[PDB]
Length: 114
Ligand SMILES: CCOc1ccc(C(C)=O)cc1-c1cc(NC(=O)c2ccco2)cc(-c2c(C)on(CC)c2=O)c1
Image (tube, rainbow, N blue to C red; front, side):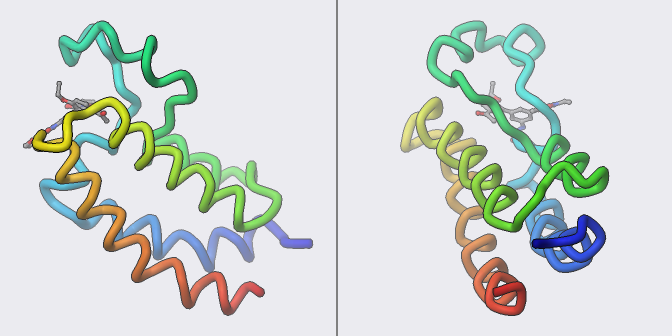
C-alpha cells in the first residue's frame, strides 16, 4: 500500500524530466484537441487519450493507488503517439526521445518503491 504523498514525492521527478525536454515535450503537455490541431480523425484511432497534464494532476491529487498505474499512463501516452503519428513525423520522433528519457529515469525510482 502507498500513501499519495509518497507516490508524488518519488514519481514527480520522473514526470519533470519529461516536461524539461524542449521542444520534445510540447506535443504532450496538454490534451490533444483535434479541432485546434487540425487532425479531426484522432479519436477514431486513439480511443484512450492521455497527456502530461492529466498525469500531473492525477499525481498531484492522489488519484494513483500504486506506482504501476502511473507508469501505465505514461506508456499509454507514448503508445498513442506512436500509433497515430507516422514513423517519419516530428511528433513520433519527439515521443521516442521522451520514452528514452523516461526509461532512464523510471528504473531506479521503481526499485526504491519496491
Ligand atoms: C497537428 C500536429 O500536432 C500534433 C499532432 C499529434 C500530437 C499527438 C500528441 O499525437 C500532438 C501534436 C501537437 C504538436 C505540438 N507542437 C509541435 O509539434 C511542435 C512544437 C515545436 C515544434 O513542433 C503542440 C501541440 C499542442 C497541444 C497538445 O496542445 N497545444 C496547445 C495547448 C499544442 O500546441 C500538439
